Image (cartoon, rainbow over all chains, first blue to last red):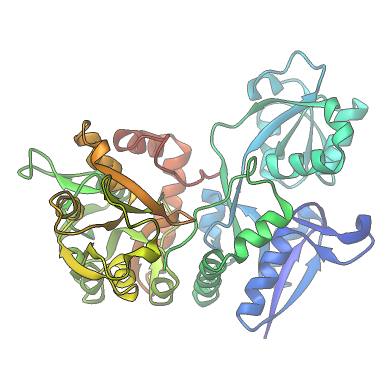
Length: 234
Length: 234
């Protein structure tokens, strides 16, 4: 009777602690999965783990659901996904006065802040960038400001949240490039609980249809900048 | 050897026969499921079936996949769905001379063309319209133009396709209302069909990532008018 959810609560606006990190867990993905659980007549339990350990807790049955996971073919082979519930676009962020980075290709031989254990850290490695590993988005941006790194590839959702919380810091950063396509994000689960997946999917449609999706979406994000996914019918 | 696909082949641009009905099946959804099948090393076999029998056909095990199905919570209770591959927006279309229909609510006691067996048919009956049953979108619009009905609730994809083929007719119609959300569209399967579903999903991700999705989409649709879904990551 519990839905067990793994997350790292240092990632606003997805998953963070209220009162500048001192209070209860909150965020878009948190609110959404809690609403799902309640509609399934389940209590939600959260577990907080460093990002580089999130998948292994799922693998070893410490919890059942991971939030905010980008869908990839390798993941689809090994895990089950909900229907997508938001999308992000990857941005190439540099200091506002940087002049030698105009594309993802220019990251070769440059120093780049990425989160250990992520797909973007692997892409940076494959580009022959020089990586400095950060604990989260905030730290990636701070490494860029301090000049430890010259760039960071960061999804739009957290970057724009950063700009809303710290608008006077905005002038220190610019977007040099961005991926041509966005990427679907879903809840990720172990293979072999079709029943749970379908139930989550069903409730997600209901949440779109009665306006609850929009209410949770508008609590965290600006619809002029961040993409939603399509709604449902019936 | 074969992927068995049910479709109704009088629905451009989704599924239709080349050379004015005489040639091969083609269309956005057709090309896409053929490309999926191809990457799975399967031959495709199409079972042409009227809209009113598409979902019952699937119940009846006459084929394994249905194309171009809107996701709804009732459907997700009973069937499996792939991740969404396109979205449509339901429009309320009337003649440009109509004076008394300004919302979906105004369809009570009006005569409306809808297709037997669809959610929009059911909606029309709930509103207490008088229903004139159409056999496809083309006939829904012709019933409207001929004044045998005063409205049809129709998705944007086929409506704009109609205008594209009749480039001087835009002024014969107006959109009086539209649903507040667009609607996710996916492949539908019998429940239990979890390995086929996974396979289709991994393949859909691949098609987005290598640009093939964009290629098929641009073949049929104007991206300034029709919504796509998010891409994937790797």
